Amino acid sequence: RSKDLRHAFRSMFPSSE
């Protein structure tokens, strides 16, 4: 899904921290 693409940004949250 294309909505899952937005979930990829969530993986950057813990990586951005």
Image (tube, rainbow, N blue to C red):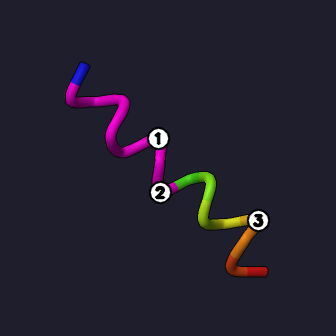
Q: Quadrant of the N terminus?
A: top left
- Would you place residue 11 above or below residue 17 in this image? above
Asked which secondary structure carries label 2, the reply is helix
Task: Identify residue type, mark 2.
Answer: Phe
Specify few, some or many for label 3: CA neighbours under 10 Å numbering under 14, 14-19, or 20 or more. few
Give the magenta range: 2-9
- Sequence order check, earlier mark of 2 and 3: 2
> Which label is found at residue 9?
2
Amino acid type, mark 3: Pro
Whether 1 is drawn above or below 15: the answer is: above
Q: Which amino acid does label 1 sit on?
A: His
Secondary structure state at the residue bearing disc 1: loop
Q: Tell me the distance, in whole angstroms, between the alpha carbons under discs 1 and 3.
A: 12 Å
Point 20% across, 29% down: residue: 2
Q: In which quarter of the image is the C terminus?
A: bottom right
Give the mark, 1 or 3, whose residue is nearer the N terminus. 1
Instruction: Tell me the CA gap for discs 2 and 3.
Output: 10 Å
Residue 7 image offset from top left, x and y in percent: 47, 41
Judge left or right: residue 12 versus residue 9: right
Residue 11 coordinates in the image, percent (x, y): 62, 54
Q: Give the left or right position of residue 7, taking residue 6 as reference.
A: right
Residue named by callout 3? 14
Above/below status of 17 relative to 10: below
Residue 7 falls inside the magenta stretch: yes
Splitting the image into 4 quarters, where does residue 4 fall?
top left
The residue carrying mark 1 is 7
